[PDB]
Amino acid sequence: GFPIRLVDGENKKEGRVEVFVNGQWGTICDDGWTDKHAAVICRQLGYKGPARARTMAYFGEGKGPIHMDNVKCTGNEKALADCVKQDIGRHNCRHSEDAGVICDYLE
């Protein structure tokens, strides 16, 4: 699987998604990023409750590589690694489109 962390949230249950790939921490593009993706990230982090996506660098932009461009998740996966990659685009993503989550979303 992939190491994952949430950064720049108000608490440890939310923030911009960073993933560790090819020796570096980097971000995930929000193209196609929905609540199903958020469920999977939050599940991998050990949270069990409802999750919600946050798009367009909601918590702030990341820096360094954008590791993944178009992740396809059913929403049921236990880990980001089990989602499937897609060649749906020429990959023009910028850090202004960095994806995020809120885990155990309340109200």
Image (tube, grey):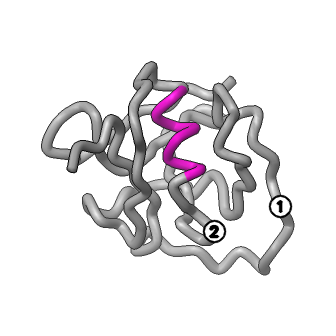
Residue 48 at x, y = what percent? Answer: 44, 25
Residue extending farthest right = 87
Q: Main secondary structure of the magenta part?
A: helix
- The residue under label 2 is 32
- The residue under label 1 is 86
Query: SS for tag 2?
Result: loop
Image side of residue 107 versus residue 4, left or right: left
Going by the numbered disc 1, the residue's amino acid type is Gln
Residue 34 at x, y = what percent? Answer: 55, 61
Q: Are marks 2 and 1 in contact (CB under 8 Å)?
A: yes
In the rendered view of the protein, which quadrant contains the N terminus? top right
Q: Residue at x 60, y 32 (%)?
A: 23
**Range drawn in magenta:** 36-43
Image side of residue 5 versus residue 12, left or right: right
Alpha-carbon neighbours of circle 1 within 10 Å: few (<14), some, or many (≥20)? few
* Label 2 to label 1: alpha-carbon separation: 10 Å
Image side of residue 49 versus residue 91, left or right: left
Going by the numbered disc 2, the residue's amino acid type is Gly
Residue extending farthest left = 10
Q: Is residue 10 magenta?
A: no
| Mark closest to the chain's N terminus, 2 or 1 | 2
Query: SS for tag 1?
Result: loop
Residue 42 - label: none
Report the front residue among 53 and 90: 53
Nearer to us: label 2 or label 1: 2
Alpha-carbon neighbours of circle 2 within 10 Å: few (<14), some, or many (≥20)? some
Q: Residue at x 26, y 59 (%)?
A: 59
Q: Residue at x 41, y 44 (%)?
A: 51
Report the front residue among 21 and 97: 97
Residue extending farthest front = 107
